[PDB]
Image (spheres, grey):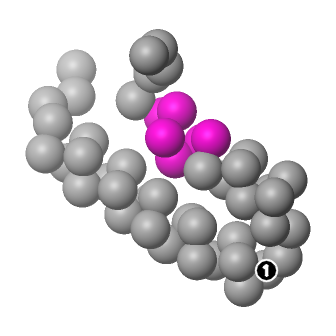
Amino acid sequence: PRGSPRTEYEACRVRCQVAEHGVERQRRCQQVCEKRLREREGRREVD
């Protein structure tokens, strides 16, 4: 597939914005996807 290093996080927020639409659910999606993002990028080396 394609994408950039923001895509998983970004698409997660978009997904849950359309499909979930709610603060609690937004927190849930954000908490996992933000951590996924941060742990992945943290495990990577940014230029």
Magenta stretch: give its range: 6-11
Total marks shown come to 1
Residue drawn at x 49%, y 72% as measured from the top left: 31
Residue drawn at x 71%, y 50% as measured from the top left: 15
Q: Would you say 5 lies left or right of 40 here?
A: right
Q: Would you say 20 lies left or right of 44 here?
A: right
Which image quarter holds the C terminus?
top left
Mark 1 element type? helix
Q: Which residue has dot 1 on it?
A: 23
Q: Which SS type dominates the magenta stretch?
A: helix
Q: Would you say 27 lies left or right of 46 here?
A: right
Q: Reply above or below: 47 against 6.
A: above
Residue drawn at x 80%, y 67% as measured from the top left: 20
Residue drawn at x 79%, y 80% as measured from the top left: 23
Q: Would you say 10 lies left or right of 34 here?
A: right
Which quadrant would residue 32 be assigned to in this image? bottom left
Residue in the foreground of this view, choosing between 28 and 39: 28
Q: Reply above or below: 1 against 16.
A: above
Which image quarter holds the N terminus?
top left
Q: Residues within 10 Å of mark 1 (few under 14, many from 20)?
A: few
Which quadrant would residue 43 be assigned to in this image? top left
